[PDB]
Amino acid sequence: KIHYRKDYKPSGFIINQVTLNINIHDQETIVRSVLDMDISKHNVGEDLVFDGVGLKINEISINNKKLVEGEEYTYDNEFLTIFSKFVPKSKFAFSSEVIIHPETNYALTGLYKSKNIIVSQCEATGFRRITFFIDRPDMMAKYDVTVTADKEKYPVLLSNGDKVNEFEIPGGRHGARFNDPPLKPCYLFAVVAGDLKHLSATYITKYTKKKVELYVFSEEKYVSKLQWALECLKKSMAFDEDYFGLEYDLSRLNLVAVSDFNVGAMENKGLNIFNANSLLASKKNSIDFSYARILTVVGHEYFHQYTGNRVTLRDWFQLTLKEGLTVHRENLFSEEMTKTVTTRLSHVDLLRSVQFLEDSSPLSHPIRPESYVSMENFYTTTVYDKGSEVMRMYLTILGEEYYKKGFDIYIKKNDGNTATCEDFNYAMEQAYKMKKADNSANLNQYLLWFSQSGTPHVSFKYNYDAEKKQYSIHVNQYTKPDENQKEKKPLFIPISVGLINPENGKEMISQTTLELTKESDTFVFNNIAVKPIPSLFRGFSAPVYIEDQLTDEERILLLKYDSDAFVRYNSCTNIYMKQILMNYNEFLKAKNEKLESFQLTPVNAQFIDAIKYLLEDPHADAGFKSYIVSLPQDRYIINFVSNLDTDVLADTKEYIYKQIGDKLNDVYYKMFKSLEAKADDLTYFNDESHVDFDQMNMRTLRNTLLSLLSKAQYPNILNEIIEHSKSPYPSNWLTSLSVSAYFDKYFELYDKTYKLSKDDELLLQEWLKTVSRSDRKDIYEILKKLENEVLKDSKNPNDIRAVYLPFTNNLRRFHDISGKGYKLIAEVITKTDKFNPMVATQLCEPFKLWNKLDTKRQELMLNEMNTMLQEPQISNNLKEYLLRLTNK
Ligand SMILES: CC(C)(C)OC(=O)N[C@H](C(=O)NO)c1ccc(-c2cc(F)c(F)c(F)c2)cc1
Ligand SMILES: [Mg+2]
Ligand SMILES: [Mg+2]
Ligand SMILES: [Mg+2]
Ligand SMILES: [Zn+2]
């Protein structure tokens, strides 16, 4: 069935109260539910239809009168239909008892068992897997929930709201009752049972001085990995108070880590549930990336308490209103917490690779789609990450003061209610009116950001009149037509700009945001004393393809002297791309024409000199440095090449890296050595509350340089690699494994690092990733070893994603012209689809670019997708996804 956004209509029913009784046993879980219901003003005498998937019915009733199957109701394992003649015309009670079995629920939706923890996941439509309901977010109800279980196995019982009773039960059981009076949609319901251990703290809110209890839970083995999470939660609460003036409204907040989770985490009210890899960390057992990851995910689920939980969604088409907005809120938070420019750079880096790829694929959709089939496939980088950039542009346009005003208007007006993207734009518009000082102003055009798919292209031409001291920036925007709009309308594009004096590097104008609202415009500046170099889209101010039309000379000057990290980083990116495209074509022609000899355009020497200049600058940022010595991501590059031959691209990258290494390897080595003291400083190694994002960026830089030096076979670098493997930091000794791929000691470090990793569940997964991404010619043989010795038949999504996804980024090997890499991943997708369709669809990610490759590889990928589509037992999720991806 296809759901269309235009078809939204309120229910003919109301659910006012939910009373749950969840009885957990070894071989089954019994769920008793009483729904206190009413007839709505929209009711037209229709049948009462509940969602209910995979439920085993013991009995159902209306007003304590048992209903009988066939006569008064039908159930088809998806919908419970109660014929209208048996539906009361006023307030009534529907009750039911069903059996479900979390033990065998490997799809990790609804109620399921993760190791020895019983946990729910109800977003988007998982509650219907637990009991009958009108499973949609505009059905707001009160919840009274009792959980019972064997006490020895499940001593900790959690649900939403206040725990209002604890009690013993004959036969070694207990129960706990939780009452949550505020209305909520069912996707925010959660329940957890297990032998959980915790850390806790008390937080006192800023304005009302309410005491909030904070609890972070895990299995006993990993309780020592809980501290950073608790710190991140405190940080999150403070930020929402300090930036947005928003306090937590409940007595208690629980964070719970489970080993089996489809995504990073879930914002269930008062009971946030996490993939263990996004909550747990220790400096001995985690790589550096875990620390920013936990900060991000804890912050994200916390900021949902307002943007998603207190202000909720009318329908699922509004998903970006809570996800784009909460990602934006988490980005503000993380940028403030890390104080490094690489935080913003890493987001943009992700958007322009992964999200830009999606938006030019057959899967392209606006951040508010017009239709869906599978809600489990709806949670896309477009909705999230382009969503966040669309939410961030409001702040760019309004500035901090008026943005905060608009945001607070949004919260005060919609608190405790459902909302739509329009409601948010409305609130922002009010601020916009105030800022520009006339109620004539509006943001009507801004709405196109929600409805129009595809990535806009923004291009530039310049003019300078030396005599007039007059400078002009001519701007053009265009979006390519696609399956969603035949004609693309001009968007409201805010362009943050500076003008750099090339002679002294100084700023020539104050902060300026150009408001491009037409297909094209000319922006003129007077009293510009000398010809500037324009600094365009500072902070990456709009989610677009920037075509700056600058010379490499200008870009080099920006890279060295501009004030904005993104524009510096983009100027470097643009220099690299021009080189890549040129060398790519040179290699391609040599291949196509089978040339015995040919020439390659060398890398710009002044560019190499600029890299050396920045690398040697003691005051420059280590994280920024690691970006400039890295070529743009493959998935960013592919946006710019038709019929991309991945082998030719691999040769192109190789040539360009070798060119730069031949000049800078001695600089690289020197820095690798000089950075060690501060990068690997052990002073705070046993203090889990002390996280230094600069220090971690130094380690990133070292590990990046070590990688470059190892590939280059720099003289005696293997010595450094071996010493690096003795480092206490997993980022370092896991790095030592992947860079040793180019030496005969690879399998020695393989075993060494495996032994270090094997007794921590999450570290072992990082080890798996490191092996998976190792640049090995025998990588297929290595993967088979992983399968037989470590992965086996694990249904843990973390294990499966760790073993295979990094490998799919191996440009040379995954895309082997035999198609064997395509064959391998499709075998994994099909296998995984039997028990977890959501994760199987995640494992399809490599195929998203299939129609962008050379015609041979297109054919190879398409063959594997058609093979998958032909599987008799294909899930709804996977079928729908592959049908859209192959334009069927
Ligand atoms: C990495 C971030 C923090 C951005 O996102 C997540 O970790 N999780 C998503 C989110 O927005 N959390 O607040 C998230 C949460 C649940 C789902 C989700 C999970 C399921 F099991 C589904 F079946 C489903 F349809 C959606 C998808 C994404
Ligand atoms: Mg404070
Ligand atoms: Mg100094
Ligand atoms: Mg396991
Ligand atoms: Zn979210």
Image (cartoon, grey):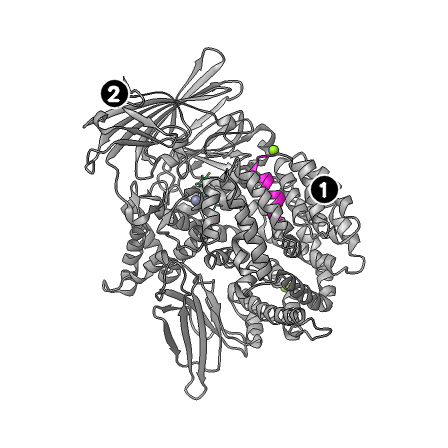
For residue 547: magenta?
no
Magenta segment, prevailing SS (helix, strand or loop): helix
The three-letter amino acid code for the residue at tag 2 is: Asn
For numbered disc 2, what is the local secondary structure?
loop
Circle 1 residues within 10 Å: few <14, some 14–19, many ≥20: many
Left or right: residue 546 compared with residue 792: left
Residue 803 sits inside the magenta stretch: yes
In front here: 759 or 518? 518
Q: Where is residue 744 in the image (x, y as percent from the top left)?
A: 80, 50
SS under mark 1:
helix
**Quadrant of the rendering where the N terminus is positioned:** top left
Give the residue pinned by disc 1: 753
How far apart marks 2 and 1 lie (CA) works out to 63 Å
Q: Mark 2 points at which residue?
A: 63
Q: Which of marks 2 and 1 is nearer the N terminus?
A: 2
Write the residue at 37% across / 45% down.
Answer: 307
Q: In this view, does 143 lie above or below 713?
A: above
Residue plotted at (51% across, 44% down): 870
Residue 613 against residue 71 in the figure, above or below: below
Q: What stretch is highlighted in magenta?
A: 794-806
Quarter of the image holding residue 612? bottom right
The image quadrant that residue 515 belongs to is bottom left
Is residue 279 or residue 133 the one in the foreground? 133
Kind of residue at badge 1: Thr
**Horizontal and vertical percent position of residue 358:** 48, 55
